[PDB]
Image (cartoon, rainbow, N blue to C red):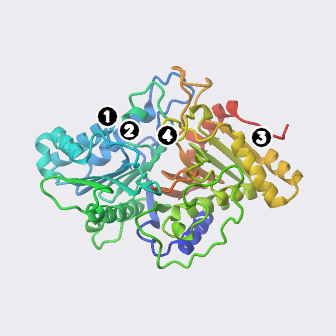
Amino acid sequence: PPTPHLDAIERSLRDTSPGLEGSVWQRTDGNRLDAPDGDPAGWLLQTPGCWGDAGCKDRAGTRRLLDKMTRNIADARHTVDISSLAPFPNGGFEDAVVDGLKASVAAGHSPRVRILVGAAPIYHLNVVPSRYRDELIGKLGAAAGKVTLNVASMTTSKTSLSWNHSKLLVVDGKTAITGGINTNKDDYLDTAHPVSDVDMALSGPAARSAGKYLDTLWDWTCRNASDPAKVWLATSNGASCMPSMEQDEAGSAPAEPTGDVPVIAVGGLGVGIKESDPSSGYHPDLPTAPDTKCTVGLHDNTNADRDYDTVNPEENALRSLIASARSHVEISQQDLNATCPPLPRYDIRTYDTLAGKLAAGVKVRIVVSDPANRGAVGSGGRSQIKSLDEISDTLRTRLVALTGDNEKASRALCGNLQLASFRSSDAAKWADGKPYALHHKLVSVDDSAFYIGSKNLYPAWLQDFGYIVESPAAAQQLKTELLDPEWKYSQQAAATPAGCP
């Protein structure tokens, strides 16, 4: 079985970050999409999972995510590895950790547990690591004696806005859940307008790869615990920081297959962890002309930093995933554009790749979160755009900058682009009046290869992680459970680009 999309991404990643192969990105064979019995698409964890129901009475998707997290932790023999954006998991998220950990202890195990959150320099942490660690020890009751805890919150660059954005659950380095879902009860659980998001669950060698990525974050984090402006660290039972928990657990045995699925695991170290990949001979010709409509304040790591790319291979893995589309690509994001300033408006190479696809006849679908979600410049608006025109206009400028002609441009753009804001039912907004907020970080290509993870396509310099899966069978499951429904309701809010029928 040929993996033409994965090959191209592997080639881009080894040219970009060879030194990080085995830690920040790794391709593996023999994985299984970890679906339950009698539900072969159960590996895809959507929330809330209530297509066609503007009232969202039955959050079956939410239910499956929480049970699947509880079960994965209840099966823990040795290690539980959790990362997110702050806060530390609360609500039903914390319950899943608690109930799973008690179950594990009951089976006679002594689980070691790392819990890592990223916090922006602006953000005040209410429940701080030591308070959270006390809370877990509290809720675990008598089982706390057999649980080794490392709890940390981290910021890696205050002046370049970089902290952990990855969303991972890894057990025994054998199972991994990942996606866009932060362990935050107010966005997903206790809401009449819950955010639309998706995780995926699998097992096998690629779970260890997510384990090694977390070892890389925790080697930085344990070490920088000496700079308390960057790291707040709390352990339990007077325990060491455990910067190599996944490596210690994997030992010398290679990971064991559990299925027949080939995966590339891929992440980024953001800014402030590792300056460059010293083993890298990556030397791109960077986008020589950025856009008029905005000028970066900060130094532009997305469009103008070769080193940043060497320690953030996820950037080029997304570009290559899209570049590898031969027939069609679907893109389901919170945004393609970032708030500018401070951050650059968009990723030039990403747009030029898509523009190229439109010029070639490859069909491009983009569903982003409703611009009605937008606020100001930061925390409060789940849309960094004022209008979908800001996406299609940019595809025009790049298409023109490609074909010179503008008639070639409008033929490429108007003939091949679908652009819409996300809808999950017929109604334009939730029953309680708030708009649909879409938090997907999803790219699917030729119904063969797809990415599910935490890296948005819009510029952001955080630490992130995800899986790129090549599997026609699995991409068909993705198409059926997520993409086709998404378009069924989202085409109502489609936008015909400026200059077309």
SS for tag 4? strand
Badge 4 amino acid: Asp
At x 31%, y 34%, the residue is 91
Badge 1 amino acid: Gly
Instruction: Measuring from the top left, give residue 142's x and y in whole percent.
Output: 10, 42
Q: Is residue 162 above or below residue 420?
A: below
Disc 2 versus disc 4: distance between alpha carbons? 12 Å
Mark 3 and mark 4 lie on one chain; the one further toward the N terminus is 4
Q: Alpha-carbon neighbours of circle 4 within 10 Å: few (<14), some, or many (≥20)?
A: many
Mark 2 and mark 1 lie on one chain; the one further toward the N terminus is 1
**Tag 1 residue:** 91
Camera-nearest label, 3 or 4: 3
Mark 3 and mark 1 lie on one chain; the one further toward the N terminus is 1
Mark 2 and mark 3 lie on one chain; the one further toward the N terminus is 2
**Tag 4 residue:** 197
At x 35%, y 71%, the residue is 254
Disc 2 versus disc 1: distance between alpha carbons? 8 Å
Instruction: Measuring from the top left, give residue 430's x and y in whole percent.
Output: 54, 24
